[PDB]
Image (tube, rainbow, N blue to C red; front, side):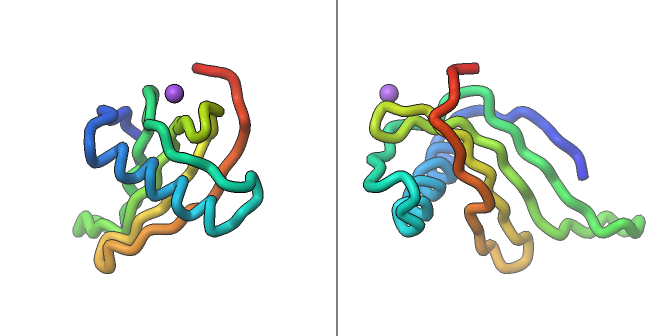
Length: 96
Ligand code: NA
C-alpha cells in the first residue's frame, strides 16, 4: 500500500458525509450532523502484490466536523465493486 495527501474537494466531502451517515447508523455518538471535511486528508492505495499493478481498493483517513465536534474517520473502498465501509470513527480529537 501507498499513502498520499489529497485535496478536500467535493469527492472528499462526500466521503466525509458518508462517514457521518454510517456513524449515525451505528449510533455510538448519538445523532451527528455533518458539517465538513477539513485538511489534512490521506488516501492509501492497495495493490495485489504481483507486478501487473492490479488495484484491489483504497483507504482514507479523514478529519470531519459533525455537530461542531472534530472526528477522525477511516473509510475503505473496494476497487471493482465501488462499495465503501466505515472502519473507524473516533473523537472528539484536537484540531491538527
Ligand atoms: Na464547523
